[PDB]
Amino acid sequence: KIFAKQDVRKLYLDEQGNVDFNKIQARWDELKNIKVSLANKHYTQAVVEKVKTMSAEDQQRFLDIVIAGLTNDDSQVGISATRPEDYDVFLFYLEPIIREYHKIEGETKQEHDWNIPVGEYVLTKIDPALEKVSMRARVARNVVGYNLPSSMDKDERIKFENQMVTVFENFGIPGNYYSLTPGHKNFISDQKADELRKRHFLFIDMTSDNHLMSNGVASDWPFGRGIWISQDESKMVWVGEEDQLRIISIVQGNDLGKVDQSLHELLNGIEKSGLKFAEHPVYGIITTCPTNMGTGKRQSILGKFPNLSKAGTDEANLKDKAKSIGLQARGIGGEHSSVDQEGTADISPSARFGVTEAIVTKRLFEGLIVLYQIEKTT
Amino acid sequence: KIFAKQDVRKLYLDEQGNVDFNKIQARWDELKNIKVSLANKHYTQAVVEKVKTMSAEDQQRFLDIVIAGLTNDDSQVGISATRPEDYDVFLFYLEPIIREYHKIEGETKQEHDWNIPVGEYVLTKIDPALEKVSMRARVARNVVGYNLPSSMDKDERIKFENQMVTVFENFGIPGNYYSLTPGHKNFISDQKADELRKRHFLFIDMTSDNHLMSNGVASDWPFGRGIWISQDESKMVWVGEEDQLRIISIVQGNDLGKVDQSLHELLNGIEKSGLKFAEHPVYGIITTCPTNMGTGKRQSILGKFPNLSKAGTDEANLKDKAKSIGLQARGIGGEHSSVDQEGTADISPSARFGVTEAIVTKRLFEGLIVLYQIEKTT
């Protein structure tokens, strides 16, 4: 029950080791009676005739870009870029997928704005009880000079971890690096890794996900994976996950602007090392899955909605109310999948593609004003 | 959507038609968000200051050397020499690019030696089952007195092809020449041409390659392009592709030295017709792309390593073992391809710049003695 890229890609090769476009089409045709991913929907005879005219190496790469979609029946998109440049090399095929998923219209491109006010998005203005709320923001990043994690061999993952350990050592924010890499100086014990995972710091074993096995993101596990955690545990960097970097700030407080400030300091510390993040001039931040591209930013709070969730028994009602407001709600759950009567949920903004980081923060705050009104009404 | 050299080069000119070094730098700076080619990395302030002091014609030539790099953000190197003298005239810029790509250290210079024995490097001495092995070799060459194919006009392509047709009719090896040049006596149809590409003799329609469009190699398609094929079909000479000549030998057999003898006889026959190959005193054989300099040679066998590759499920183990003894293992479908289920892999000698042809072939044979011993004892 393991669908590793290196094995499943061979199902779409001929006897000479070249890409067999007949086997690719046969598989998409099987999947039409099951579920049509965007990869399948935008895969046309014109796309095929184009790819057939490209170098053998680009044809093999093209197979690696759709392999997740070919392997996983449940794929919505089914696309994994292998390198920063893939969004340009294969733009003829990738652009319609990006534009459909992100519902992009006209001349829209990604803009950026980290000039986010402090002392304005203050949750106590909504309710005095919102003094100490878990406020969370992260950005996904990939680094110019590396393959994306879908296509990094063991040596490249070790090289990438080694460069990032040097950045954390030297970027001037106190904290500690914990490696999953056997033989690394910062190697974590099997007791420590679960322990950090149970404190909700450390990502899970990626080899348990067929999507990440099939697109190469889970390859060479656990070589080149680890976590940097700041002294105060407000800042952390995941190394070697689905994107090379998951850059995270978690602040207990009431000002959304503070979690953005904390995130920007961490981002700026990594940027000052002189490395560059992979960014497309139209579609913004480059990620392995095109669903994450633009800002690569997620932002949320953990709120308590006992009224809308009926003491944690009607998550669907909380989700439907959050949706009515342009927010997304995910119930956290009690210990051992018990009912959480506090109706604790992760609340995040939905935003149109291309909006700045500063606008995402504003939309979360404005949405929370209304969600807490209907929570307080019910 | 424009890739043709004569169109894209215009984006780097000022209002007077002179090369704009601010426009070149602005483009390299954009590319730093995606991929840094060797052309970009070695484009230093000292390089710019030197090119600004050269003649208008040399500055236009300089733009023509980097244009593929400026245009195609997937470029690893992004250099196309326009003639053999570029490797002297622009050495101040190109030398660090050559030295970085080929990992050249100290006073290394290319040496040559085609005194390669027949009946010594015989694979059946390793194992009697190695009677019929796919053995492949190719050499790229350009000819003194001609521009490189990046900058030949239609008339020069026709003149070059005319020179090679007379060489082929008179050089003592039996074979047929097939021309894509309309009006040539050896002209072939699009169907006869597609049958040659499908049996893997004839090179691609180069106008499908953005790199070759941007660097001028694909200009005036298909004038002056053709293929000589030997009567027994084991030998061929591509005319007018990325280099003026590509000499290919593909033999099912067991004697590495017989493949080298084939190339040697073709090279000698051409030289015996009064043609001299272009060569740099340090960096050896002159090619359009600096990555093909030195010998201009690639050689490999297809071997089966089911034990090292665990029936094709552990390619990394085979590549690691090959690398430990000075060899490179790849899939059977080129770069970024797969080892098949019988452990079939392309095995080539690891590059070490400057080593003679005779020593490389010796080191491949000796490498294979060790590799097959590792395979049989795994």
Image (cartoon, coloured by chain):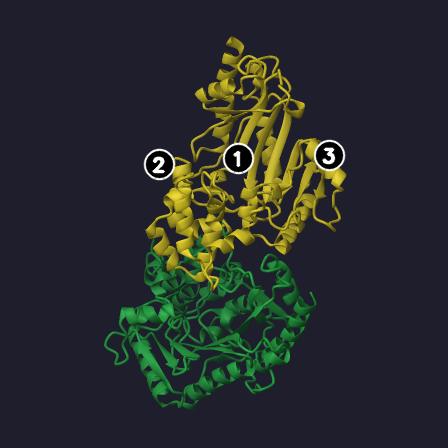
Chain colours: A yellow, B green
Q: Chain of mark 1?
A: A
Is residue B66 something one can see in this rendering?
Answer: yes
Q: What's the distance in space between the residues labelled 2 and 1, CA to CA?
A: 21 Å
**CA neighbours of label 1 inside 10 A, class few (<14), some (14 to 19), many (20+):** some
Q: Quadrant of residue B216?
A: bottom left
Q: Quadrant of the N terminus of chain A?
A: top right
Vertical placement of residue B63 versus B132, above or below: above
Indicate the amino acid at tag 2: Glu
Determine which residue is flagged by label 1: A297
Q: Residue at x 32, y 59 (%)?
A: B7
Q: Which mark is residue A105?
A: 2
Please indicate whether residue B337 sits to the left or right of residue B241 in the image.
right
Please indicate whether residue B180 sits to the left or right of residue B91 in the image.
left
Residue B16: percent from left, percent from top: 32, 59
Q: What's the distance in space between the residues labelled 3 and 2, CA to CA?
A: 46 Å
Residue B358: percent from left, percent from top: 58, 82
Q: Mark 2 or mark 3, which is nearer the start of the sequence? A: 2
